[PDB]
Image (cartoon, rainbow, N blue to C red; front, top):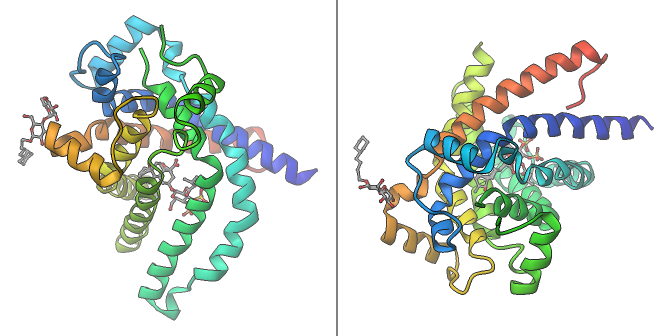
Length: 279
Ligand SMILES: C=C1[C@@H]2CC[C@H]3[C@]4(C)C[C@H](O[C@@H]5O[C@H](CO)[C@@H](OS(=O)(=O)O)[C@H](OS(=O)(=O)O)[C@H]5OC(=O)CC(C)C)CC(C(=O)O)(C(=O)O)[C@H]4CC[C@]3(C2)[C@H]1O
Ligand SMILES: OC[C@H]1O[C@H](O[C@H]2[C@H](O)[C@@H](O)[C@H](OCCCCCC3CCCCC3)O[C@@H]2CO)[C@H](O)[C@@H](O)[C@@H]1O
């Protein structure tokens, strides 16, 4: 039952990190998809910034509201790690490389590997991300829970509603991984600084894809939908300008530092309270 303990405790760790990150995560998602909310009459007025969003959301909805949708984040660990344990090792065997065999080969193989594993994961898991996203962007709240989101979205758009924005998310995974490993190699506390700068750059450069993905998610249950990722992109840029793609980026970076800090702290607390850390 050792594997069970490692599994569940790892899930507790991930749950801690995601729960801590949750409040600033929602602010990012609100600022990012506020035009969609305006379209769906879920928002009364465009936000002025991060502080505005925090203040308004708090005073109007409450404090607990900041952890809305986080349950999806918590229960996401188990199917992902089940898939992670099952196939990630075997997939790496198919595409992986030691740097000595070739840097180009290592890079490309790493891209293909991470992309394929990520896609395989999303094939089972993407719906949870959809639910999280739809629950984050609210306020009579449009949705009343995970199950409500699923049932209603299935009732309106069927299965495709749950998997909307899949391709820009995959492309996003590939791009993000490429930037991450590239920057990681280029420049290699010191560890905290490196991790923060790398993560920040990689996530920032790959952000518009994420925005497209999430706003495509938002169109589920609506009469008007984007005709693919490129169509979405084109319409967003035409209507609101290029900067609109980067809406909520800074809040996401704040989620970054927050998450890194919390996960390091909790790792320390794990070494204190338990013999070994479960990550
Ligand atoms: C278009 C985008 C933007 C760029 C790509 C992704 C991630 C950043 C992509 C990121 O993708 C992660 O990248 C990591 C660094 O390479 C990689 O770690 S590593 O392989 O050990 O090196 C993770 O692989 S895993 O096996 O450990 O789990 C991988 O997560 C996945 O592939 C699982 C999928 C279910 C996502 C995961 C994730 C994260 O913020 O971390 C997450 O799902 O939480 C995404 C957020 C959403 C976007 C943002 C997606 O909307
Ligand atoms: O806040 C007002 C508007 O913000 C966004 O529009 C941005 C666009 O997204 C954005 O692409 C556009 O850019 C124009 C400014 C160009 C910046 C020049 C850079 C030079 C280098 C240093 C940084 C700035 O500015 C618009 C504002 O006039 C939103 O997309 C709009 O919906 C919103 O009405």
